[PDB]
Image (cartoon, coloured by chain):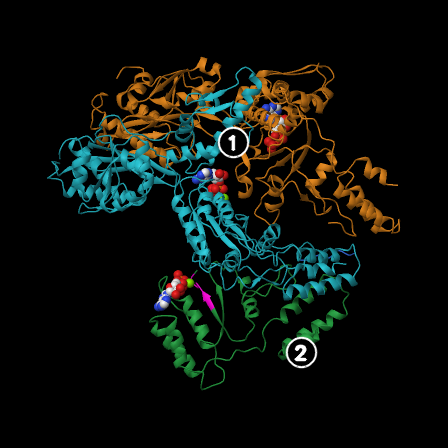
Chain colours: A green, B cyan, C orange, D blue
Amino acid sequence: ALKRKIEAAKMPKDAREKTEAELQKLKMMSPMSAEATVVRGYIDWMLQVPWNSRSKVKKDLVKAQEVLDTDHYGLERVKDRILEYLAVQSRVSKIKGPILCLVGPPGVGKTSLGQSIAKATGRQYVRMALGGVRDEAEIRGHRRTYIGSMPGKLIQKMAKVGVKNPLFLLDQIDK
Amino acid sequence: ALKRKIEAAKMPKDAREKTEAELQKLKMMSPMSAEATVVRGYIDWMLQVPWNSRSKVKKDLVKAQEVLDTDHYGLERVKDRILEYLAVQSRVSKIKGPILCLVGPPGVGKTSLGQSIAKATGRQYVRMALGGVRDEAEIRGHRRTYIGSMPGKLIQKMAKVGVKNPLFLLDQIDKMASDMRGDPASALLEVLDPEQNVAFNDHYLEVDYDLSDVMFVATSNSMNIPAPLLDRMEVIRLSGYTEDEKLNIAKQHLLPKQFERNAIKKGELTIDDSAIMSIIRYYTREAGVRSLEREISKLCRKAVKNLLMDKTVKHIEINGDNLKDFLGVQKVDYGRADTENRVGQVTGLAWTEVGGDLLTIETACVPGKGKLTYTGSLGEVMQESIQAALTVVRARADKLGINPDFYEKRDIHVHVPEGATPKDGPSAGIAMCTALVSCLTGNPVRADVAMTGEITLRGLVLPIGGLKEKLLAAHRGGIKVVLIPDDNKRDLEEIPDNVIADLEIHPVKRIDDVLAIALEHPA
Amino acid sequence: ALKRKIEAAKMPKDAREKTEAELQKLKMMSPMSAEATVVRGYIDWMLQVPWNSRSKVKKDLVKAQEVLDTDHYGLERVKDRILEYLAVQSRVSKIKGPILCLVGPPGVGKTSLGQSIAKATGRQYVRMALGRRTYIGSMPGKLIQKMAKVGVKNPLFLLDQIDKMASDMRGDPASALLEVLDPEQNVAFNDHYLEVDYDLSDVMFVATSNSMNIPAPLLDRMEVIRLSGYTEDEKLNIAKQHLLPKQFERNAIKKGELTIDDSAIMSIIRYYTREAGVRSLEREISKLCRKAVKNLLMDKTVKHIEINGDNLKDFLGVQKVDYGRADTENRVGQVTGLAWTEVGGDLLTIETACVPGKGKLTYTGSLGEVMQESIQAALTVVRARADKLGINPDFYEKRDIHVHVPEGATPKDGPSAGIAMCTALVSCLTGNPVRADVAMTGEITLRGLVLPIGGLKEKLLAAHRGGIKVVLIPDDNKRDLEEIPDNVIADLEIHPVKRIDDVLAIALEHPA
Amino acid sequence: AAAAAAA
Ligand SMILES: Nc1ncnc2c1ncn2[C@@H]1O[C@H](COP(=O)(O)OP(=O)(O)OP(=O)(O)O)[C@@H](O)[C@H]1O
Ligand SMILES: Nc1ncnc2c1ncn2[C@@H]1O[C@H](COP(=O)(O)OP(=O)(O)O)[C@@H](O)[C@H]1O
Ligand SMILES: Nc1ncnc2c1ncn2[C@@H]1O[C@H](COP(=O)(O)OP(=O)(O)O)[C@@H](O)[C@H]1O
Ligand SMILES: [Mg+2]
Ligand SMILES: [Mg+2]
């Protein structure tokens, strides 16, 4: 039925066992139903969340500083920070993703700089505008008991890219 | 058997694959049930979507100029900017820059410029009204887990147009509520963000609809735009209207569309232009011409009802005297110039969002213990400007011929007569100072001189904002001389020459330039 | 079978390839099944839709004038606008521009204007108060259902209380009714139950509301007609001509036993109720009639019950509210200003006391800040004119001044009654009594001018009810004297003034 | 056909 897309997704143990318990629960249900529509919606979300997909990141530093110098001018502390990350990254396999906070005046070049870091480190790019975010349901979402229930907006952009290592541009934190 | 309409629609990959799958499911299933209503609902929403239907645009700008000059009047900077935009679209063929934002007071032709851009380019017009948008799922849609599920208004208005490239008018991007369930500014961001327009995600359709073809323009009354939306907009900033501009809008555009709407032919009704000027000055206080549509439409309708229940007069003519018979008593009145040179009274220039008004300033220096009272719903910035002006008078006390103990010997009151109307801002400072000097020397202020300017302690006159409505207000009120600061002299190259030819504008730099001109006797 | 019924009304051709389509589908199914009940229901909910049979709209305007005046007394500007709409409706056979809207407080008859317009235009009345085919069975939409029930192609439609339609909750958006209101999207209104495009042109729309709190896609198409509050003579004429007979017929009181006099009704309006409409008056009149019926069953001796201004304390309880009167019995150092509000008008006495002291200025009576600013402006006018009024000019430091307005715990604010307070200050400083027969309104400035005010009519009706003979209005409110009833003009000696000297010449009994 | 209450 849909186990071909579950084993086609190469899920980790808890997510795989839970989605195959949900799909095994779905077969003993009668179709054309409400709760079967709920279960097909939940499986439809867990088949499009990235579990294994990883982009190959750039090891070269001269080409990297060439990229961040071709699309910006003189943001030396940030470009130094990205060369620090790409210098550590060539010594190990995986690192915790760096959590940065670019603070400055308007028009100083913080969003296009995120595009530059995305194009230079090899990662993929998506941005979440935090201006106007007023409740936790835009981050954690709602339970699937509710009618209009979606997995927040972090998981929707993780699914919108389709990789395990993107660059979230959490834009306008102070808004 | 809808198998030939999926191939007839020529849909992309995920659209064809989910519709083929949906069709098979429906086919296996039983008709007339509510689940077949949901499924069959999903197919006939997935067939109204314009997946490949494109309208041809036009690439000529002489014809676009002579379309935009009709249906409107005097928006030459705005229409100039639009012709720059269509001048760009003849070479790039898809704009990757910002979105045209039409900002102005209520009544100016923002939606009608949406229709005239849409007629000028060659595309089909559509308008998505906002204001009632609280949900993010009102723009993105709901999913199909609920029995009654229907998509958001973006792809539905896209479905009633049926064209891949329409001209959306996001109307009233300012007006939307605060109690918001989701974040519609993020959805309205991703319809306007060209990296996120190739992949737009409707929650009902659950497919990848392309919005990298639609021309968006939006309207606005102010700039209470949410934060992620504001950096994607290009503001054109429609300004207000004069009296002769409203007379030519009503003369060339509002009367022929209300004679035709009430089926008044040419031998029935003749509205004199002084009646239109009387509706502008006396009945309405708008910056646009919507209220001119209200009183012109009501006036034509009363002419119709008189022509039915009279049957003797066949040609009703409405001059400036007969409106009191038709539209009733006069609702408002504008402030105008004073006739003689009063001592304490100084006419200032005030700027509101419905236009510019005059601003009378009375002061009174009576012999007392030295206490100053400020009345007239004055803001704190105004009161600080008044005591700054009084500090200027106390520093220049001996060369103005003023007895320097007036801080201790004379009570001072500053009143602005519209006591219920709140008012704030520094832009009356050099007015106030003049009034104070005029009450501390007995030197009357010549009543044909209005003035505006922010005063500082060393006497200099700082610039102010919005000379256009203030010079239109002094033009309307019968003022002959306006004293502006020097660095607002730049704004004199954006004023219609009826005002410059009518007024005698003197730029000032310090307060001695104000006191030399504005007072009768030499200080 | 059913073919003579579907051709008996001569439905349009599209809906008859639909109707004959489910008829030839009905030929190939079982009769007793519930799916056939859905099919026969879908046939039945198309042969009731009014595809034809219009109502002949009426074109003359004199009989429309009187058939508007047969059920409503004093909505003259509204009735003017309706006859103008019927004039352009007489020439233009299909007005599809904006839509009539009746904004006003509850109590005035904006809902029953749907009835008076309904039999005034000649069309049929359907009222809508706002505030898909399947196996389980479905009714058609509300907009279409009213049309089918009425069964006429041109039925007046009312959108009542759109101020109470759009709440703060998830409900109806503006879409499904502005697609009804707009002219170009009414040639094809495909109802979701029928999936057949049905026209909505030549259907008159009237929407009623209590404010302009209307959704922004709807306020673009609604002409705001305002309905002001009824005066007391109008409420007497509405109670006597239109409201006593409906309570008599809903209580079954024959005409021989109950007599409710005019002084009884004016006693209810003045003493027993405070509203803009005539609804609370009908609660009082209905209570009066049912107490008459109870007093006829419980006493068979008397039969005719006479109710007048004296025996409305035997009925209806005791006097709940009261209004202000002219204090004509003496002429003292206080003035009588005029106050305007939503229920109507009120007299507003203003008192000053000027004792020897240090110059303290005390303002009292729940005064708003704009009123206190008007007292300071008026006192500045007195200080600027101290010599020629006869005042010793050192009163700013030698006499304490108190300005009180008597109804405490009543919030009072507004730029008006400035010249009244200036008159009271000149009075208590000079010892010159203000003549009690003079009410006053206006706004004072430091130069001595009198600026215009608002709500002149209710101030003049308050002054006429109070026993005032002389009213001092500003000059620029002479215009508003073009809409005063001529009994009120004939009883009030109205003096339009423009300065404080014209005020103090009239309002003070001694020359200054 | 059976009704079902959702939250
Ligand atoms: N150092 C730089 N070199 C090259 N381009 C720059 C630089 N700084 C800014 N820019 C340009 O300025 C434009 C706008 O800057 P950006 O939108 O990044 O400002 P921002 O810091 O995000 O503003 P805000 O803080 O208000 O969001 C960008 O398109 C970018 O190309
Ligand atoms: N410059 C103008 N020339 C001609 N007509 C105008 C002009 N400005 C406004 N109008 C008329 O006034 C009306 C204003 O409507 P709209 O632009 O929708 O108001 P808003 O922008 O406040 O929503 C339009 O119907 C238009 O015909
Ligand atoms: N001018 C009038 N003449 C006669 N009766 C009136 C008049 N104005 C109001 N009424 C009565 O007052 C009542 C007001 O009720 P209605 O208008 O239906 O509610 P709402 O005011 O909420 O729209 C009506 O039943 C009507 O009988
Ligand atoms: Mg930014
Ligand atoms: Mg608009």
A95 relative to B44, above or below: below
- Whereabouts is ligand 4, in terms of quadrant? bottom left
Residue at 31%, 35% (x, y): give it: B498
Name the image quarter holding the N terminus of chain C.
top right
Q: Amino acid at mark 1?
A: Gln
Q: Position of residue C312 (x, y in %)?
A: 59, 20
Provide the residue span drawn in magenta: A169-174
Q: Return the residue at label 2.
A: A7
How many callouts does the rendering have? 2
Identify the subunit bearing mark 2.
A
| Rendered location of residue B170, percent (x, y) | 51, 50
Q: Quadrant of residue B30?
A: bottom right
Whether callout 1 and callout 2 share a subunit is answered: no
Q: Depth check: give the residue in front, C508 or B280.
A: B280
Q: Is mark 1 within 8 Å of ligand 2?
A: no
Viewport quadrant of the C terminus of chain C: top left
Q: Which mark is residue B471?
A: none
Q: Which residue is mark 1?
A: B258
Question: Label 2 is placed on what type of residue?
Answer: Glu
Give the secondary structure at mark 1.
helix
Residue B80 lies, in percent from the top left, at 40, 48
Relative to B260, say whether C511 is above or below. above
Decide if residue C211 is on the left or right side of residue B418. right
- Mark 2 burial class by Cα count in 10 Å: few <14, some 14-19, many 20+: few
Q: Which one is nearer the viewer's eye here, C406 or C39?
A: C39
Q: Where does residue B91 sit, x and y in percent of width and height?
A: 45, 58
| B20, above or below C137, in the image | below
